[PDB]
Amino acid sequence: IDAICSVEGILLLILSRQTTIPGYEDELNKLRTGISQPKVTERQYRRA
Amino acid sequence: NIINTITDGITYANRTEFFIRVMVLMMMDRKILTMEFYDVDTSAISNT
Amino acid sequence: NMPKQTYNPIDNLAKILYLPSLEKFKYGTGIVQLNYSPHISKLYQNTNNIINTITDGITYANRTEFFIRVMVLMMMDRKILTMEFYDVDTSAISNT
Amino acid sequence: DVRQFMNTTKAETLLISNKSIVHEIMFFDNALQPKMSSDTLALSEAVY
Image (cartoon, one colour):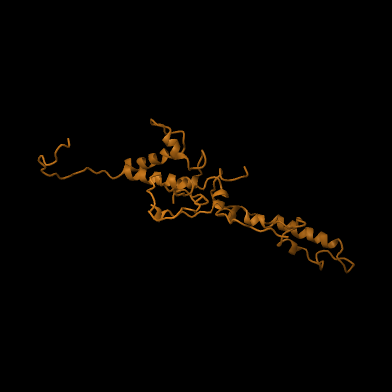
């Protein structure tokens, strides 16, 4: 269960912008540029 | 390979993908470094 | 007079967004009119046999039986539309 | 390194794009250009 939660957490990290803000909030923003929209469709999420 | 979008050439998407994969690489794969030394005396002169 | 296409760009999404349309209104059409589709235009026969009529022509009875057929079709034809989708960019698109 | 300053892209395609098609460009450098041989008559060639 720790492993599956870790997977889900890594996934949360780079989707759904307004969740992750550890200490930088800037290069994370740099990263997120590429999802093309501040909302992601499901099938994209599932395949990811 | 990770973001199913119909695109024209290369644009921010390969960059995002590349970030994800190098990230997930470094998150995994713990290693600790073991090296091997010599016995140099003072031959290495004048160079502190 | 057709125009020429120079400077061939990359079209990895034109073939999904435009090409099916753009050629229907390609530069050089005089009129574009609305019509019934095949699979319905075939319901418009000549020999009227749902409604006998004393004439040998294309009289109103044609229109009437044509109504009857499409009406009883639409009585039936319970269909459900299902479909998948692509996912494209939105910043690299002119139309909003 | 003049022997591999190969870079082929007609400015047409550079100009007709889709506003995010990020692509490659090369860049030479010769600021430390050594004097030419003691034979060359006169460099009468344009390198715009």
